[PDB]
Image (cartoon, rainbow over all chains, first blue to last red):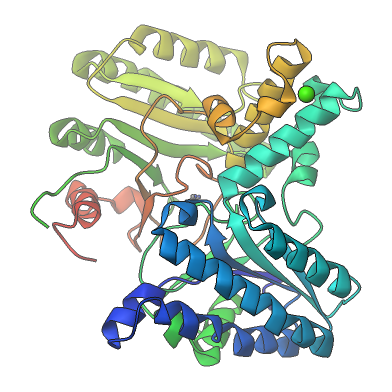
Length: 226
Length: 213
Ligand SMILES: Cc1cc(C)c(C#N)[nH]1
Ligand SMILES: [Ca+2]
């Protein structure tokens, strides 16, 4: 059995830049291109959802030049992906705190989501200015606003009600979470959504990650591979 | 790597079962680990047959009674997290006695997660925040990570910085989702009944960087 929803923490970009004696942020540039063969593998295999950790709540405290580079790379990625989403019938979504993002980038994100919302072969979600803690607290805020409008009785808040307010609630739960780069950490990613996820950790750095290893991780989840 | 700092708060998923804890608790006190949180009984464990649930309730009662004299001798604080509404009345009264007799103890904090789930914990926090909004204590617009985190269990203790999972599975099982958001993860094939203080110490040293995986 194939995982219904795969999530990826794409770590090891800066380490790849130092190892291959590359320029500043070249690992992020090489890293952005690794996603296309994996997205195509997902749609051809039948994976219904893929969620990638592109920019965390914590990444806002990285050196400002890295933040600027990541915003430019996200803008470039969205433009490049829109025709690919249309070609492969993939719905493109974004999760995260949009208040912290550049206004023009939010406009581009809105366009991409709107133009691909009717696509149904797979859902590709890019987590931008995202953190599991932010997501959970935002869901708590929306539940409390509903209490304030008199729509919900606070005494009736439970797991089943709360789950409707967390990001990607209309998608299946994350059943496989991959982390490249060699670190054994969830790093504030999909905390709620990945509550029961199987985990796949690898020393392979993100710009070196292949479809063969991604497929191996899928087969480790199924039981096809050891 | 000149300074080797041990984790301030260790959490353990005690898997592989289908007394080990006592020397691990003593090792935390010896090495300066401030808190140890262990996953005893999950939300998911209520879905097991009634005779199994009854046996688990007996084991929990036995364990609490046996631990109270140790908590007093070593001056350790004993706490419990999880949904108490589902538990028997005499067990809840026992949990209350143990936590009240030891609440002021400062050597370390031992927390036992009973009828616990990370999702339950988070939704419980959302409920209390919403109740504060309904009573006019706060406006819903003030709800952010900084306010919300106060309502998540164990927020007065350091964040979980090391999470050990015995039993060989590489998976998340609805245990300290919020609290272990940045924790280093230690996975081992060792089954919980066979887990040693030597291996527990190895995990502490993998965290500090004194030893490698
Ligand atoms: C945050 C987190 C990591 C793991 C392995 C768990 C559990 N259960 N929670
Ligand atoms: Ca208001």
